[PDB]
Amino acid sequence: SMEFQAALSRKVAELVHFLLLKYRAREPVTKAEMLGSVVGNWQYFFPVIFSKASSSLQLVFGIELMEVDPIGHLYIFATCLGLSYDGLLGDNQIMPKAGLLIIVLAIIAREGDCAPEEKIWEELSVLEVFEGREDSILGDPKKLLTQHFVQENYLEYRQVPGSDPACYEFLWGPRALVETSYVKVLHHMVKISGGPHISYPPLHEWVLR
Amino acid sequence: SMEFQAALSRKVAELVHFLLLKYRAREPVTKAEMLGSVVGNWQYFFPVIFSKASSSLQLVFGIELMEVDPIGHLYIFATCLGLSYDGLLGDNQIMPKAGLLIIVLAIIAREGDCAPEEKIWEELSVLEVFEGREDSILGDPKKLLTQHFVQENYLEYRQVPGSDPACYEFLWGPRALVETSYVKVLHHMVKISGGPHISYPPLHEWVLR
Image (cartoon, rainbow over all chains, first blue to last red; front, side):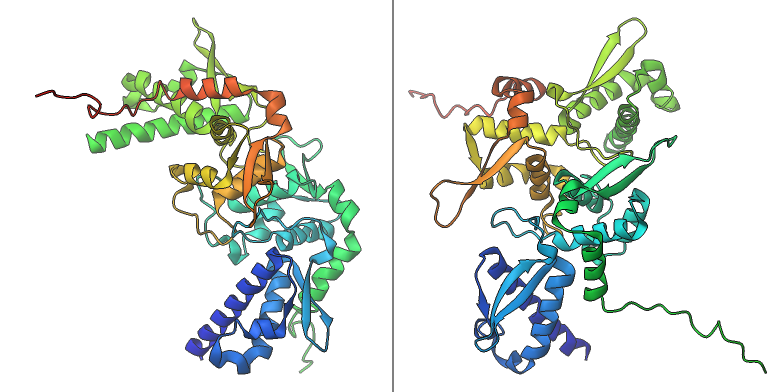
C-alpha cells in the first residue's frame, strides 16, 4: 500500500512535470502523448494518474487542462480565471504562481474589503509548498511571494488607517479587479475544493434520556 | 581565536540587527545608543564591532550609515545610490534588497547593454545569502528575487533577439536608468569592495637562468 502508493504518486508527479513542460511551450497535448510518458506498466492506471495530475494542475499551480477534442483526446491549457499572470520567467524551472495568487485573493474576498496581513501569513503557513523554510536569510518566502503579487498590481498593501503602532493589510489591486471578480474567485474556491464541510458533530442534539 | 571570533561576530550581528531596526523606524541613532546595545564587556571592542556592522550594512543590505554630527556622534541612514526601493514590507522581518539589486545592475553594466541570464545565475549562486536553497519547491530564490527587480522596473527581462531555442537576457529597466547611472553603480562597486586584485602571479617574467 505505502510502497505502491509511493510509486503511483511518483508517476503522478512525472505526469505533472510533463504537462508543465507542455504548458511552458504553449503546445497542445494528447492522451497518446501522455501514455508516451507514463512508461510501461502504469498504462493500466492512466485514469487515476491523469485524474490526479489534472487536479494538481488546478489546485497547486492554477492551471486548467481543457479537452478540446473528445474523440482524439486533445488538451490545451488555460490559466485559472483567465489571469494574464502565471509567475514564470522564461524557461527557468520555477513553479507557476497563479494558484497561490488566487488563494490570497480568496482570503481577502472572504474577509471583505481587506484582510490583516497576519491572517494572510497564518493561512499561508499551513501550505506544504513552503516546506519549513520560513527562516530563510533572504526573507520568509510566503511574504516575498505576496510581494510578487503586490508588485504586479494584483494586490495592494497598506497601513491600516489610524493604527498606532502601524498595522498593515492587503486588498485587491486594480489588476485583480479588472481581470476577475469576487464572485468568480469565491466560486472557483468552492468548485476546486469540493463543497466544504467541518460540520459540528452531534453536540447540537439532546439525547433526552 | 575561533571561539573569541565567534563571540565578536555575534556582537557584530546584534549591532547589525539593532541598526536595521533603527533603519526601519527611520530613527536616528547615536554611538551612545549603540553602546546601550553592545551589552557589557564588549564596550572596549566598539571600534571594530561598529566598523564591521557599518560595512555589513553597505555590502549586504545596501544601506549607508552616515554621520551627521561628529561631536555628538549622531547617525542617519540612506539607501545606497539613493534608490527609492529597499525591498521591505511593513514591519516584517525581511532583509533589505537594495544591495543585491545593485549587484545585478553592476553585472549588467560590466557586460554592456545586457547580460545573459546564465551569467546572472552563475554570479548570484556564489553568494552565501542563498544558503543552498536553490531546490525550493516554490522556485530558486535568486531567480524569484530577480523577478522582484523586474517587477519594480529596475530590470527588464527579454528574449535574446533571434534566438532559437529561446534564450533570455537582463537589461537596466527605466527606473534604474532614472534613479542612477552606469558610472555611479560601477564606482560604488569599486568603492565598497576596495580596489580589486587577482593579479597574475610571476608567470609573466622570465628567470633568464
